Length: 127
RNA sequence: GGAUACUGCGGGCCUUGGGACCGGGAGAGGCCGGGGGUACCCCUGGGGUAGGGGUGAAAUCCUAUAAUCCCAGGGGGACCGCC
Image (tube, rainbow, N blue to C red):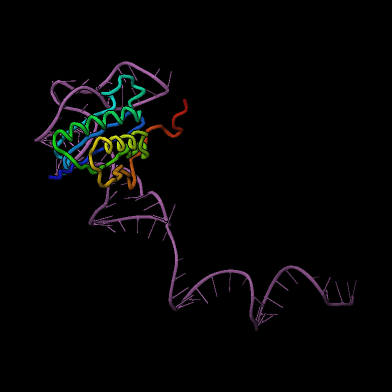
C-alpha cells in the first residue's frame, strides 16, 4: 500500500540538513546532514554533499517502507537570510532519483510581520 | 503772513487684505481605552542520534546530564512586513 511522508530540507549558506518524517512530522525516520558525508568545514553546503545525504536518507526511508514524500524547504529566516542555499535543488533531484515519488513542494521559511532588530550593528559588516 | 498735494491728528464711509460661520469631503496630525498578527527567546513532554554553529580559512563556543532538527503545549518582552 502507498505510504507517504514529509521531507524537511533546511538549507543555509553553511550546511544542509535533510530530515524525513511521517505526515504528522511527529516521528523521525531518517535524518542526515552535510557534515557527516564530508570532513572539510568549507564543503558542507556543497550540492554534492546534499545529493549524497539525500540519497542515503531516501535509501533508509525506502527500506523502512516509505514510497512517497511531500517536501518542505526552509531557509533559516527570521532575522537571518530568507533565500535558501544552493543545496535544496540538488537534494530534491537526488530524492527523485533515489526512487521516492514526490508530491507537493512548498516554502515554509519564517517571515516576521515585523521582527526583532538583526545582528550587525548600525554600519553592518565591513571586513 | 500765505498754501494744502503728501505724512501726522480728529470724525464718517467701503470691501479687495485679514478674521468668524455653514456645507460635503481628504489625511501615518495628537491623546486615551479595547482587541489582535506573525516572528524571536525560555520552560515542560513525545521522536531521533552524532555532530551543530561560525569563517576568506579557522578556532573559542553548544553538545551523550542527548545538542542541531521535527511535533504538542505553557510563559515573556519589543515591534507592526508586503500593499
